[PDB]
Amino acid sequence: ASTSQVRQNYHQDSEAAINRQINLELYASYVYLSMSYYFDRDDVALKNFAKYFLHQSHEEREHAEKLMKLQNQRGGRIFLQDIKKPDCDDWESGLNAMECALHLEKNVNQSLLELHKLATDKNDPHLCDFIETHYLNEQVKAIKELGDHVTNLRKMGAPESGLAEYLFDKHTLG
Amino acid sequence: ASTSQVRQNYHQDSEAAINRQINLELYASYVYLSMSYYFDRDDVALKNFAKYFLHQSHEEREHAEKLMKLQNQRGGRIFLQDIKKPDCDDWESGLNAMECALHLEKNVNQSLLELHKLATDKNDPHLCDFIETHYLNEQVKAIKELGDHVTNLRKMGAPESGLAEYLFDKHTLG
Amino acid sequence: ASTSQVRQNYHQDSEAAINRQINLELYASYVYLSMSYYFDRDDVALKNFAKYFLHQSHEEREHAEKLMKLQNQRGGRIFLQDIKKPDCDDWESGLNAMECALHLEKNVNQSLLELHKLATDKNDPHLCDFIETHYLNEQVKAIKELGDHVTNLRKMGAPESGLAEYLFDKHTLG
Amino acid sequence: ASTSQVRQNYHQDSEAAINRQINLELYASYVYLSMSYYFDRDDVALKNFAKYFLHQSHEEREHAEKLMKLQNQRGGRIFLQDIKKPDCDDWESGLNAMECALHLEKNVNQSLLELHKLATDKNDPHLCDFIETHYLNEQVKAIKELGDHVTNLRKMGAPESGLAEYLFDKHTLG
Amino acid sequence: ASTSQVRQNYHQDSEAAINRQINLELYASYVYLSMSYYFDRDDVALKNFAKYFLHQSHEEREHAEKLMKLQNQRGGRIFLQDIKKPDCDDWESGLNAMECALHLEKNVNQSLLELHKLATDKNDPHLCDFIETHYLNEQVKAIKELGDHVTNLRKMGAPESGLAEYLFDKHTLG
Amino acid sequence: ASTSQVRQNYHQDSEAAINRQINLELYASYVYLSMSYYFDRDDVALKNFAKYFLHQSHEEREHAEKLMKLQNQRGGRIFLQDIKKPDCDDWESGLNAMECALHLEKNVNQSLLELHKLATDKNDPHLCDFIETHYLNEQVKAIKELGDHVTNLRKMGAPESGLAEYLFDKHTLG
Ligand SMILES: [Cl-]
Ligand SMILES: [Cl-]
Ligand SMILES: [Cl-]
Ligand SMILES: [Cl-]
Ligand SMILES: [Cl-]
Ligand SMILES: [Cl-]
Ligand SMILES: [Cl-]
Ligand SMILES: [Cl-]
Ligand SMILES: [Cl-]
Ligand SMILES: [Cl-]
Ligand SMILES: [Cl-]
Ligand SMILES: [Cl-]
Ligand SMILES: [Cl-]
Ligand SMILES: [Cl-]
Ligand SMILES: [Cl-]
Ligand SMILES: [Cl-]
Ligand SMILES: [Cl-]
Ligand SMILES: [Cl-]
Ligand SMILES: [Cl-]
Ligand SMILES: [Cl-]
Ligand SMILES: [Cl-]
Ligand SMILES: [Cl-]
Ligand SMILES: [Cl-]
Ligand SMILES: [Cl-]
Ligand SMILES: [Cl-]
Ligand SMILES: [Cl-]
Ligand SMILES: [Cl-]
Ligand SMILES: [Cl-]
Ligand SMILES: [Cl-]
Ligand SMILES: [Cl-]
Ligand SMILES: [Cl-]
Ligand SMILES: [Cl-]
Ligand SMILES: [Cl-]
Ligand SMILES: [Cl-]
Ligand SMILES: [Mg+2]
Ligand SMILES: [Mg+2]
Ligand SMILES: [Mg+2]
Ligand SMILES: [Mg+2]
Ligand SMILES: [Mg+2]
Ligand SMILES: [Mg+2]
Ligand SMILES: [Mg+2]
Ligand SMILES: [Mg+2]
Ligand SMILES: [Mg+2]
Ligand SMILES: [Mg+2]
Ligand SMILES: [Mg+2]
Ligand SMILES: [Mg+2]
Ligand SMILES: [Mg+2]
Ligand SMILES: [Mg+2]
Ligand SMILES: [Mg+2]
Ligand SMILES: [Mg+2]
Ligand SMILES: [Mg+2]
Ligand SMILES: [Mg+2]
Ligand SMILES: [Mg+2]
Ligand SMILES: [Mg+2]
Ligand SMILES: [Mg+2]
Ligand SMILES: [Mg+2]
Ligand SMILES: [Mg+2]
Ligand SMILES: [Mg+2]
Ligand SMILES: [Mg+2]
Ligand SMILES: [Mg+2]
Ligand SMILES: [Mg+2]
Ligand SMILES: [Mg+2]
Ligand SMILES: [Mg+2]
Ligand SMILES: [Mg+2]
Ligand SMILES: [Mg+2]
Ligand SMILES: [Mg+2]
């Protein structure tokens, strides 16, 4: 209600867009958590797939926390919503999880690009710089890594080859 | 569907109760995350309250991950639900957050005690030992610490005394 | 007069705006110097307030020097004006100095945002990047820190409570 | 042909502009290589001019490699063209080489500024940030250093003074 | 207004003279700052002249801070005035800057000698000792160093010899 | 034009042959650079193939620089030509790149053997020794390594087996 003493050049629309991005980062954390423990099942048993996705889960929680810090730095107010359960599901294989992660990271990137366009439209260079510095190249590198992983699994003969996913687990994710 | 090759003495009801406890631990992680960033606001500005609740948030995620590992160890199947947004809210003060945390940790403890009673009724000593070893004394210590904190804040004159919450932030949580 | 051999895509208006920002950074250095020695008076005697503002004074001189380096890097010509004596004055209390610093840092931020808008209008991405990298987030962090300090001093009971300012001097600025 | 699985918000025109910039960086590497070995001639014999330009040659190859990495990160396709032999030539003196390098680095900067304007027109903030972070300030510093070197050689009395170029070789480039 | 609890044998006239000397030291800091960045220009490009005068600028700020500390130690009240922009200007050469610095340091010395004569007339031995200990020999050494530098630049053939200023920059200020 | 003061027993034809070999070494550097970034594509994604060919690219630039040094040591004059874009192309697979590299290194070897025959015909033992010491055995080892790599990839079932190229990337080039 009462205006923040710190708030300056921070549009109400940008404040709301940051709250939506916090929810998306927490959702991405949850998707990777679910994917991690699929690979920990006794009938899947690919421990480096499990470790890879758990690390990715922890990284998304860090991405959400940094946006929460930004909201307070600019004098906005954090508004939280439910974190939806992962949608994608029936994980099925290493290849199918990697394809789900690729799609997730491209959707997160599209959200960030819309956020950047809003910050540009409201002439908020601090928020533009925040998104560019901490998010956009991190998304480009994540998308490229996931594409590389999908390519290798497809060339090795996944998902039909259980040997392909086993050897990728050792040699790329190990 | 098809029975796990590892499953032994693990009742369907226990499997479902563990899924419910995973959701509760993730919910508790979310409540502490919300409480943390309230204290990071420029109009609250109690950085050791913020750090204390963030650490508590991270600990609840570890509690959820260990239950997910247990579900797979016993040959159950993880089933995830939405993580509800925190309920409590309007954080208002250090004292009121500490009282909300005390109530949260007592509800989590009551859930664990119901889980233990189910495991006892299904003669599952491994699950009883898991809950006793990793959860019950961790809840007793958390509840005692939170009661201690509430007592000190009340005796110091919180929430009316902004000096009380400031000095508690430095001397107890610093 | 004669065109710099280094100058490229550097508008006369941007050159003049950088000279105005150099003067403002030197003015901010002078305001913090004055505020520092107020707290060194024998009838004020808050040594960590004094040290805090002296450090802030030295940081503003660094901000001015970096803009002088930028002017020469781009082939502009530094033009200096008098550094006005601090306006605000009658320092009165730790809280009132912190409020003056908050207002100063918000005015400096507004100057930087106008500078960024000019650089954007003249399609000068190097100057936009310079301002974003070295100034805009440094202003957001300074404003947030000063708001946090004002909040704590108000909650502790400043300026009426000499005990509040004494204890803030030890515990936050010490 | 078939769309990259990684490509997102990456305009065909930006892809082609990056290929043109790769060629220019390789061309700049070649110009500095040629300039280096001129100073290694027995009838020129200025070993620190030779070392300075060789280092600059190696740096331009790094600039080209980073753009090739960017093209693949964004899901574009590298397209290579011949690397033209250096144009400028008849090196003649330390001063004349430094003037050729100044002109080269200003042309490379103008190419980067056109690339940035295209990325801005296609609302590609990742590519704008890439150019700003890795190229624009590196060009401003190179241009300023080369201007400084040209100024000193002119003031010392180059190119007529072989003593000027000898002493600059020892004291500035040594 | 109300007499300091610390003030003893500290004449109103001495208090005012110390305020005037604070302004002069800040003015000298500003003159050296301006001189420093002249040598950082791409068409001057004498980096050790730039570093020498920047160090001298920082030293004058220390001289001003020590006088501000003295004013408070004795129970006087600091009164600040605008810091005038440097007068001298059109820097023109290393030799002309060194001559301006020599004239500045002789004017500062004359101010200190007038301050000492006032302190002697008011029988203030503490203030006499302060000026003698911290200022008078520091001025004699600065004046002697600047004379030495002017002599060498004149003998080497400055300002006509750009080679003289270049070699002095390397060998004396390097 | 005017004869070098250093030139002795260095035939005009040898001087021209060395200039042609400089161009070929730069061309080989460019072929390996192109091959490297093919393996960095998201739809190829063999990072140790990429690293192997990038190292080979850097080694060819060193081979060109050493010939440029030789030309100056003997008092010849470096004459540069355009560096043609790689010819071979459509890289297609690890095996096909390795076969292109084998063919490249055999053509470079044939050029060196023609250079040696010219140096022998002009009774230039220094140039014969230079070629033998720095180039001929380096070509024999490169050709043997590339043949070994082609053999292994063929035996493992490349190019049809994406598993063969993946495992060769880890075990031979990793
Ligand atoms: Cl507003
Ligand atoms: Cl919202
Ligand atoms: Cl909701
Ligand atoms: Cl990458
Ligand atoms: Cl990167
Ligand atoms: Cl059963
Ligand atoms: Cl369930
Ligand atoms: Cl649900
Ligand atoms: Cl306890
Ligand atoms: Cl205990
Ligand atoms: Cl205390
Ligand atoms: Cl112009
Ligand atoms: Cl101006
Ligand atoms: Cl003025
Ligand atoms: Cl902050
Ligand atoms: Cl930050
Ligand atoms: Cl204490
Ligand atoms: Cl498209
Ligand atoms: Cl193209
Ligand atoms: Cl071509
Ligand atoms: Cl620079
Ligand atoms: Cl810089
Ligand atoms: Cl010398
Ligand atoms: Cl008196
Ligand atoms: Cl006065
Ligand atoms: Cl004034
Ligand atoms: Cl002396
Ligand atoms: Cl002495
Ligand atoms: Cl001959
Ligand atoms: Cl030739
Ligand atoms: Cl050609
Ligand atoms: Cl061998
Ligand atoms: Cl061998
Ligand atoms: Cl292995
Ligand atoms: Mg959403
Ligand atoms: Mg990640
Ligand atoms: Mg994320
Ligand atoms: Mg649902
Ligand atoms: Mg970055
Ligand atoms: Mg529940
Ligand atoms: Mg806990
Ligand atoms: Mg818990
Ligand atoms: Mg609800
Ligand atoms: Mg125990
Ligand atoms: Mg102004
Ligand atoms: Mg500051
Ligand atoms: Mg500043
Ligand atoms: Mg005035
Ligand atoms: Mg921008
Ligand atoms: Mg930054
Ligand atoms: Mg071109
Ligand atoms: Mg360079
Ligand atoms: Mg370059
Ligand atoms: Mg041509
Ligand atoms: Mg930068
Ligand atoms: Mg005066
Ligand atoms: Mg001095
Ligand atoms: Mg002084
Ligand atoms: Mg005036
Ligand atoms: Mg005496
Ligand atoms: Mg002494
Ligand atoms: Mg050829
Ligand atoms: Mg090789
Ligand atoms: Mg070679
Ligand atoms: Mg062609
Ligand atoms: Mg040998």
Image: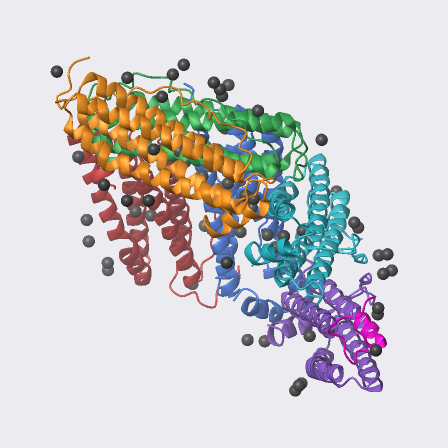
Chain colours: A cyan, B purple, C blue, D green, E red, F orange
Q: Nearer the viewer, residue F9 or B133?
A: F9
Q: What stretch is highlighted in magenta?
A: B1-20
Q: Where is residue D99 in the image (x, y as percent from the top left)?
A: 34, 22
Ligand 3 sits in quadrant: bottom right
- Residue C126 in percent (x, y) is at 53, 33
- Please determine whether, in this image, residue C25 is positioned above or below residue B146: above
Residue D148 or residue C40, whichever sits in front: D148
- Does B16 appear in magenta? yes
Q: How many marks?
A: 0
Residue D151 in view (yes/no): no
List x then y, in percent, for residue C134: 52, 43
Taking the image as drawn, is residue F156 in sight? Answer: yes
User: Is A15 placed left or right of F126 in the picture?
Assistant: right
Establish if E152 lies above or below C32. Answer: above
Which of these two is toward me, E145 or D24? D24
Residue B41 on image: x %, y %: 69, 59
